[PDB]
Amino acid sequence: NAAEVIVYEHVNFGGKSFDATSDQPGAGDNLNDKISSIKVKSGTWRFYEYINYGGRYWDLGPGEYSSVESAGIPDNSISSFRQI
Ligand SMILES: [Ca+2]
Ligand SMILES: [Ca+2]
């Protein structure tokens, strides 16, 4: 049940995706300023608008977000995220 989150390039879980089980100070593999949908498999994750956990943040618990905006997150703006 280790914390896990999958981020996607396009809404509705499309495009490039990255399965994270550890903290990402750069938002993963080439997904900086591109994340549009997210799937929190387990744990609670915090998403930051700037790399290295900078700027405003949003905390998302287990569940699926076909559009990051449904989570109050601006589209194509996540730059880093970590478990909390
Ligand atoms: Ca996008
Ligand atoms: Ca950003």
Image (spheres, rainbow, N blue to C red):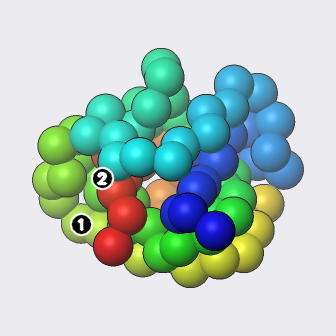
Residue occupied by mark 1:
56
Q: Secondary structure at mark 2?
A: strand
- Percent coordinates x, y for residue 68 in the rendering: 61, 61
User: Dot 1, crowdedness within 10 Å: few (<14), some or many (≥20)?
Assistant: few
In this orientation, which residue lies closer to the viewer: 77 or 47? 47
Image quarter of the C terminus: bottom left
Q: Which residue: 17% across, 43% down?
A: 52
Q: Which mark is residue 49?
A: 2
| Alpha carbon separation for disc pair 1 and 2 | 6 Å
Q: Secondary structure at mark 1?
A: strand
- Percent coordinates x, y for residue 63 in the rendering: 72, 75
- Percent coordinates x, y for residue 49 in the rendering: 30, 52
The type of residue carrying mark 2 is: Glu
User: Dot 2, crowdedness within 10 Å: few (<14), some or many (≥20)?
Assistant: many
Please indicate, yes or no, whether residue 69 appears anywhere in the rendered image. Answer: no
Please indicate, yes or no, whether residue 80 appears anywhere in the rendered image. Answer: yes
